[PDB]
Image (cartoon, rainbow over all chains, first blue to last red; front, side, top):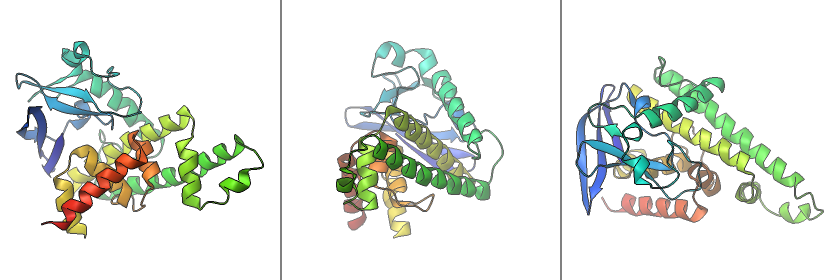
Length: 198
Length: 62
């Protein structure tokens, strides 16, 4: 799945179909992406057997479930409220979860794709999400260091800041996982906004 | 290699391109560890590394 934003109003979408074949759909509207485009890094669209629909596929990932698809179950995949009819550009499941993500971003002081924005405000949003990532990387090691409070902290502390951050992240709680999932989807949103506002 | 990296990203899927944007700090300015990136994608450090390698190989040829 590759969405190319051609200008503020127009995109094309290239998706796998079957065998070695991909299909490119032109005249893809940028206006409504929130209603169709999955923000989750654990999913992407493929072209449906008959070419009318874009259908979700779960990638191999430890990220949380979204859109009511835990893994690839064609009851849900083929179902109308879980896919996007091409040219209609509406996927209720995707829209529903996207909207939670949007509200979260609004709560963090980030600009959102459903309200007005321009290049400057998106750029400021990337500034702010970078700040969130950094603070987060501080908290992750803080929490790991408590756990895991053994006097062998000296061993951990024999590493560089990066190796420490890496080991803490590797070993972290599911809660932390949820924070990074959320932030990844918000990042995807801000990027769609950046591209539309170029 | 801002333009060349961009031409490469154009040949990747949304997911792979965003792995690399995160990694190289193309949007927020901050480069990220393979572990931060892997956490954002729910994949291992190694898978992120393979994506990065794929991109470097594409970056070399045309």
